[PDB]
Amino acid sequence: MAVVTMKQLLDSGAHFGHQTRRWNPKMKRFIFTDRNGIYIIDLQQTLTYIDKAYEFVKETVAHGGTVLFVGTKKQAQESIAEEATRVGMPYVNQRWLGGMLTNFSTVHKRLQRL
RNA sequence: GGCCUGUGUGCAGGUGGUGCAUGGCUGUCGUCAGCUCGUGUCGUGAGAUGUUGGGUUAAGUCCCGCAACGAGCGCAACCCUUGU
């Protein structure tokens, strides 16, 4: 089950993946072969985990949680802020701090101070 | 009974020792800019991190990027005198 289709997907560049001096997995199941020393995006895994992410993440999205829009890159500060102003959800701008998400009971106190 | 005369009984007192038994008080490094805690992450552990690195300061005073986020006791300042 696809989402929307190939040519009006293919418009703006589909072949990404980085530099060559850095790859480290082991995964022959996602590694293909050399031409001009660089790879192409993965067909079967795109489709299959598109479907699986769809079904289970809909189940949990019905189970009902929420996520901050923490957006940081200078490429997308205003873009993310615009969509976040549209969707109305809270957001953050600049930096991921070391050690909040575990030590939450004192950013609780930063909230009281806020 | 106030009171003081004695008798002795409880005694009362020490500038006699331990300041290395103690408290209190005080000088000193030093009015030098630092010294710690929370909760966390790291480390088997002693411990580290924060408090490293630049600009910057009378100074851990301040800014910027980061396993740190935060804070206190400090340095500043409301005190006195002088200066209009």
Image (cartoon, grey):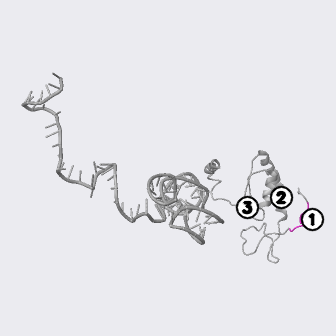
Amino acid type assigned to the residue bearing label 2 in the image: Thr
Secondary element under disc 2, as helix, strand or loop, is helix
Q: Are marks 1 and 3 on the same chain?
A: yes
CA gap, disc 1 to disc 3? 31 Å
Chain on which label 1 sits? A
Tell me: residue A26, above or below residue A53. below
Residue on which disc 2 sits:
A48
- The x and y percentages for residue A74 are 75, 65
Q: Quadrant of residue A30?
A: bottom right
Please report whichever mark, 1 or 3, sits nearer to the chain's N-terminal start: 1
Expressed as whole percent of the image width and height from the top left, the position of residue A24 reads 71, 70
**Res. A72 mark:** 3
Residue A71 shown left or right of residue B21 in the figure: right
The span shown in magenta is A5-13
Q: Quadrant of the N terminus of chain A?
A: bottom right
Query: In the drawing, what numbered circle is on residue A65?
Result: none
Q: Is residue A9 a member of the stretch shown in magenta? A: yes
Indicate the secondary structure of the residue bearing disc 3.
loop
What type is the residue that disc 3 sits on? Thr
- Which callout, 2 or 3, points at the residue further toward the start of the chain? 2
Position of residue A19 measured from the top left corner of the image (x, y, whole percent): 76, 74
- Mark 3 crowd level (few <14, some 14–19, many ≥20, 10 Å Cα): some
Q: Nearer the viewer, residue A89 or A27?
A: A89
A14 or B49: which is nearer to us? B49
> Which chain is indicated by disc 2?
A
Query: Image point 92% across, 65% down: which residue?
Result: A7
Q: Which residue is mark 1?
A: A7
B68 sits to left or right of A81? left
The residues tagged by marks 2 and 3 sit, at their Cα atoms, a distance apart of 30 Å
